[PDB]
Length: 51
Length: 50
Length: 50
Length: 50
Image (cartoon, rainbow over all chains, first blue to last red):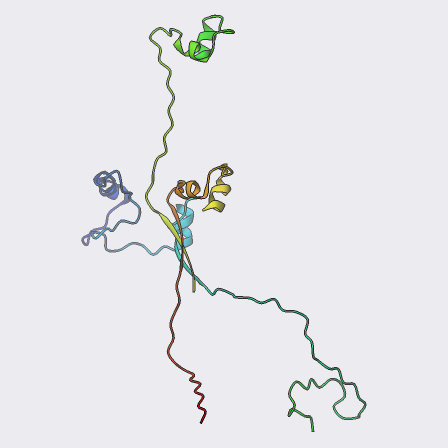
């Protein structure tokens, strides 16, 4: 995010803020993150397994 | 098991079907020769072996 | 409430439904409720025939 | 929707089609739509008698 590397524990604050911001009627699923620019390449089947 | 969200669109043709019944009007012609032994499957009038 | 009344040894063989509900409980309240919780649209399956 | 509800184990015997239709699905939506696709003229058959 912004030419800075973040650990997962580092981004815990951001994800917690994201869950706190959303209202009750809506869900968190499929929400844009314009701040983030890059993620390590990871396949779809691995994502399904992790989920 | 919960997986990734699924959005799927499917297109299909309405297969209007009339049942296929046993074929009628075919002839089995059996003959003797020394050329092109076996069946020849003359489905067309002008398709004739030489 | 029926279990609690049996626990104190009261004779409830003849007391009927509403009468059992009327019985004094002594600062104890027993309540049950049912609800259905909505959720967001997550998986959409659309089938189109041409 | 009926197949999904029965797969979960609901008793849908007495509830009607209208009643079955509102039944909660839990983040799943099922829809079907019918369309007819036009095409451009490609073969023209004209018959003229004198």
